[PDB]
Length: 252
Image 1 (cartoon, rainbow, N blue to C red):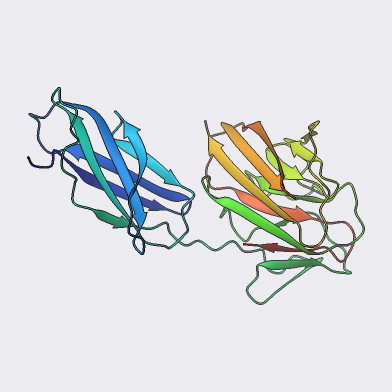
Image 2: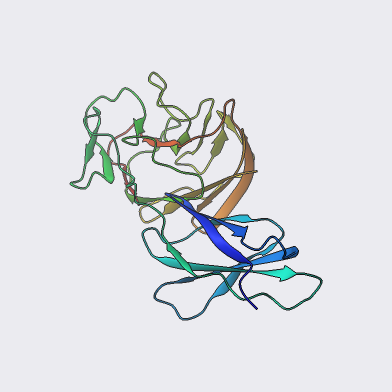
């Protein structure tokens, strides 16, 4: 036969790709759709979605790597999958994660992705240079060097770049401290992760279900919890704070 569905839209975004398809033959009666992808460098397609929706959000894909997508459909009362759409190639976009420049208390590396708490006074949180955390991304930090821990230490993500506070342990923010404590809108939760040392990584994965599901992983343990935001979620900031010198954090 001939293909009853084609890919209509590909939305390339920093944290993934949205694929949308449309029926190009009104006379076909669709029950289910089947979406596959592969890296353009790879031989083999894999199913990512089988269901009756006409769009699917593809997450957790290597950024600025080309992927190829194809879709087909089942229906008309039969069980054979239709022929495939023409394939379409897409990639996630590139929005680099970088620290703010010129914030007193922190010195950055050349590519502005490594931040060191120096010997100067600091007024609070070192934020990302802009809100470049997009839900769907895995945001990874690595501790390069350590200093003395302090309860105001934090690494996290938040809705706004707010001045004044000493840490991200505050409303409309999620973060971990250097003792492994996890804070949601400024309230610590019971489950802890292992305290960070040099070489430790911390990852944040955030998915929407105003209410987000957050996974934080560090030192091969993870916590998963709900994060309630008081307004609609857009791109987020990330940030860190360290009271004492010597803490050095790389963001990927």
